[PDB]
Amino acid sequence: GGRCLAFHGPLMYEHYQGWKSSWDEWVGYDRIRAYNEENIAMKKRLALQIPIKLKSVLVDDWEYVTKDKKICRLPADVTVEMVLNKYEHEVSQELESPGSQSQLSEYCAGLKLYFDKCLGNMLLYRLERLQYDELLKKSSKDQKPLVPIRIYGAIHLLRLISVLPELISSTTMDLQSCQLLIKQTEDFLVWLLMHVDEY
Amino acid sequence: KKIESNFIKQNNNVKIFAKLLFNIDSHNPKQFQLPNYITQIDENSIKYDFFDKIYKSKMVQKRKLFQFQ
Amino acid sequence: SRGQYSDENDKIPLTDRQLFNTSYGQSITKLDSYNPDTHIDSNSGKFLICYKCNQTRLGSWSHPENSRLIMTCDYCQTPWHLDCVPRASFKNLGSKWKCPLHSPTKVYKKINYKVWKKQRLINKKNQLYYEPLQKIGYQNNGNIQIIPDFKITQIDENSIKYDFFDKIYKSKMV
Image (cartoon, rainbow over all chains, first blue to last red; front, side, top):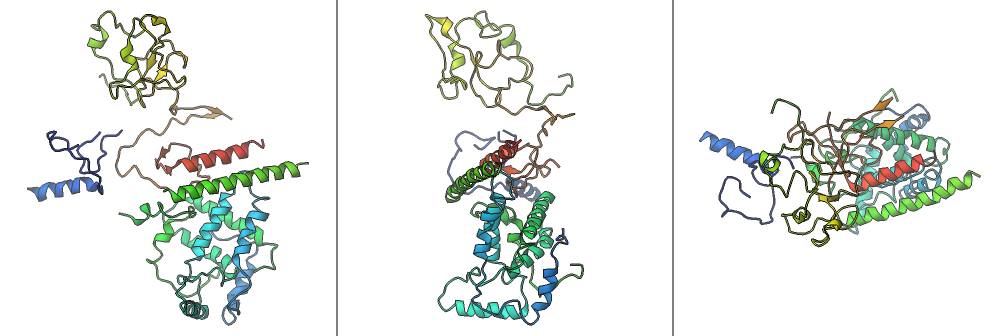
């Protein structure tokens, strides 16, 4: 199909066109088009925001990170694995439409992967920056990778889902993807509306 | 040539947002602020995933036929 | 020739050699005499197996009546019997013979109606722009291509079968 599809320099392929049969080769190597190497080097050089539903918690923990940082225990007993695993057990069975739960499940996997490396880039204040530095220092004594899943609570999770939509538009992407992201954001906030005890 | 095109051939379970993961080093971090307004192995993995989700679909089908009564 | 529209749907007009001076045994169509050359392709020499019934049905020279006419496709070269799909004879002049397995150019769903006369075809340059980012719930109204503005997203098998299953799980409650 088409009129120009060649791994090497194109010669209106639909074999080296315009040459004799004693030049063919079908070896398997790397293939780059490069538009006939820039036309044989130019002929040899010429010859969006969150809804107002429960926005009190962000201004609640905005002041509380100045001197308390919303966490005082390094091995925090609050963890994200159970609160993320309960999503497939309470709401995906109830609120999601009949069909596939992928829009929650692969979201959970992707957000875990995002939380695996979100540290060091935004989402951080100076004193818990020092806390993360000392956590990395105590985690480097056994040359093990730092897992931020067992040592970080869910207090920064909703602040993360608050900061991401503004940076979502920073890259080139379609608009209904952002519509799906704000739909997931409102779903998460109606999930956490009456879950005021867990943080 | 753009880096992201061959990045999706080895990344799994991250589908919704992939373009923002490339330029994580092109933007410098800053302090906290707030506005005043406020494929073979991966193929087997996704087949096993799909099997899990249609099984979950079977129990949710049982769930709506149970709660319909 | 005179300045009319002609996409790939129209077949190239036949030359007079195949049209007037095509002997007496051949005739315009294979509808007469035994023609076993139509059941064997010159590309590989194998037998054209019909898609609907898995039979070449070449028949016999002693019993010509058991021979079933077959034709190759003008797009995918898929063999097809003349008795399986409802059709009297071959397709030699006019539009190219589109086998009943391809996407129609225009479909009709009644809710007045929407035509969706495809999206034509864009040549390989900067206007033909691709973006794979989402597989689930895209609502991209078709016009796709399979991989292992007039944008065409890189759709794969997994996403198509996923959103098909998702839609038929939405629609069965109705």
